[PDB]
Amino acid sequence: SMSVKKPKRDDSKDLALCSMILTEMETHEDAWPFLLPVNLKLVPGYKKVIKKPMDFSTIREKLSSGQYPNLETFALDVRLVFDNCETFNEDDSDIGRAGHNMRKYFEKKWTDTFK
Image (cartoon, rainbow, N blue to C red; front, top):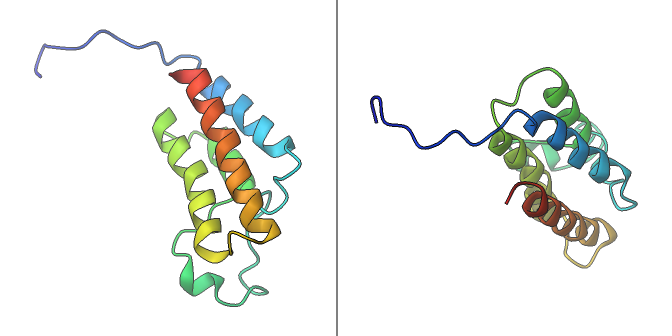
């Protein structure tokens, strides 16, 4: 409360560490469905159904331009990529399976880096 603060968790490395995690996600062999924004002209249904599209290239640009206020807003966008994927793709499809694999990979790196 006013003039009463918990001890300051060091966040000065968070930008660098999120950049490293994002590089590892970008270079995973199953990243291909997620590298670029879904083409809203060419993929019927996507525009209407997926209210907030997100992809790795868009996260990379937001990261590089100071558009994440803290490390939690960065994790929210990464999770959005996988939540969108599960909304639009069957579990038993190459893309559906890619999404599950990537979400697993991310969540381990997140825990190991920050928790």
